[PDB]
Length: 503
Ligand SMILES: O=C(O)[C@@H](CO)OP(=O)(O)O
Ligand SMILES: [Mn+2]
Ligand SMILES: [Mn+2]
Image 1: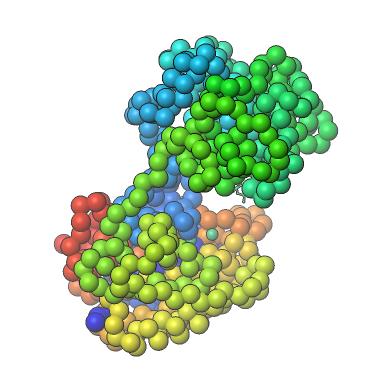
Image 2: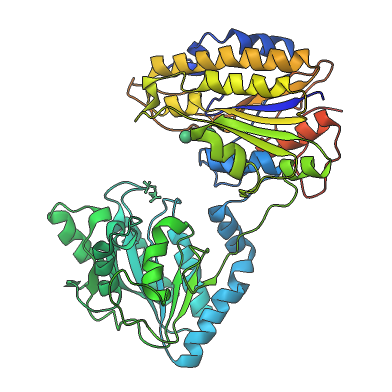
């Protein structure tokens, strides 16, 4: 068996400036020799090319999903944005049923969510689209329960989103703020139920302070030293008639982890965090499915990915190995397989333990040498068709925002890379050396401060096949089609990416 390997250098991208660029400052002779001998291009790993909004840096989860799927895998924000822009949203069955529920019970429509443009948990423009829909179907009025951010956005920005939303209410002729809670309260994820109860009591017009306007209560918080995230939940005077039997709730958050708890309070009949009298005939709609214990109608259902690279390999009777250290093991397993834990037939996996340190600058080599030795051990068995390998280090050490450790990390990876790839080449196989998004290409601001984040830069691709030229650009969703090309395996239609290899 001639092996073909995808070797993912996590958080390793192409950036022109050398300043604070560990990728360019590192001595990486093995990478450079392959780069100088073999065909090379660069592909996009951020924004719309990976199913994220324009301007948004790529990441490990999204990047490994796109890589394994061989297509653009649209994430929640973009999917909902596109649904709005193209009209589907306003036809959505769950949203129109929530409105039929209100109209048929003469009851009230409530809207919960994180009122910012952070884009991690929500996007407040989706609130405006719901208000437009409610107005269109004649709802009359809509109680909006605002959860303030200050964490995925500037710590004191709530007043701008509140102002703009107040103008929407006037413009569209519908809706009002009913309650206002910092996300510390409404969006806990550590089962601190006393924080949640305060949000719940405001939303319900039970126990809470009241202010005449959303602005007033936020400004009162500011004057006390409590910024957006920490606003103590409050009620907006005369604008909150409670959540009563017959009502409907739409929760526009799309990220499960911080929306689940509040949703359990309203809509898990088994909820025991604190004692409640649940609303009867409550229509409870969540933008996504937050967990299995919430009785909700799901506005945007999870889409399963058929014919990821691993499934195609299976269906061609090929064997495959997924391998990485702990820190990127879910990436090369679960995410690579399209969000599936189960092994395919023919699949085996190798987990190497990551060191137990708070920040990986303390051991820049991490477990890269043990990953390399496990891999050499597997390739010496001679029974692998496909290998999916990730070297975690450039991303994990780069997050430290420290240049010398990040350089050392890349240099350790380079030494391992040369042993892995030379072995693949002795076995008459092929490697694609690339990345899932950038990070280590920039670990310093232009003013020499630590920079601890991913980048939007395009990622390198080297394909260790002679006599071929690569296409000039492309995206992560093109990698799996390139592996299939190298394996001489037919690409199915639902893999819409294109081989980077020119024919
Ligand atoms: O709550 C979350 O999941 C987001 C914050 O927007 O990340 P973290 O909480 O870990 O900052
Ligand atoms: Mn990554
Ligand atoms: Mn990262």
